[PDB]
Length: 177
Image (cartoon, rainbow, N blue to C red; front, side, top):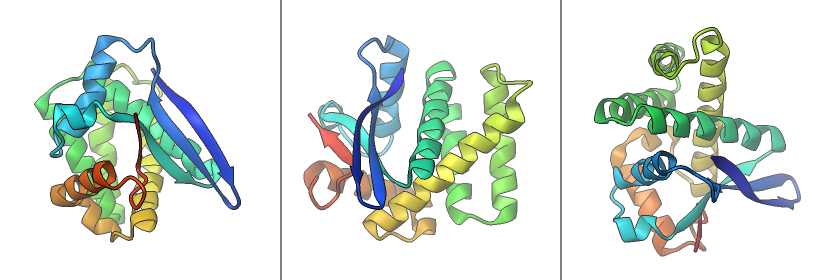
């Protein structure tokens, strides 16, 4: 499953390290890998990532945690290129940030959540997903000095991930093994 593997409480912000637990089944591990494989990293580079670090207030990072929990469950149970593409479009729409863009993203995430069994709870689970994605985009924009809308470009995410592998001091997005 997705766990919080480390917490740093420094001043006005908190940083949570998010990663997979040791008892993660093979479908969760494969999903973890595909979150990154689709964005320019080799298998050997991905195998070096122990966790993803998120930063903000306690309320902000908790929101990010629940977005990542749902992202992983979607990827695990609906593993498919069609799913990856819908998830990319939610990210694209959400980085643009307009009201109609987020309404369209909400409809996409709702169909995915229903497909994994969140039916009676789809509305609240969609809000949880989208709120946490929005805080996560806000965190990447502020932390690494990237226009939020630019984050919706595939080339921006590849660049960011690759810089975080290479220079994990100037780009502390990952904990490396």
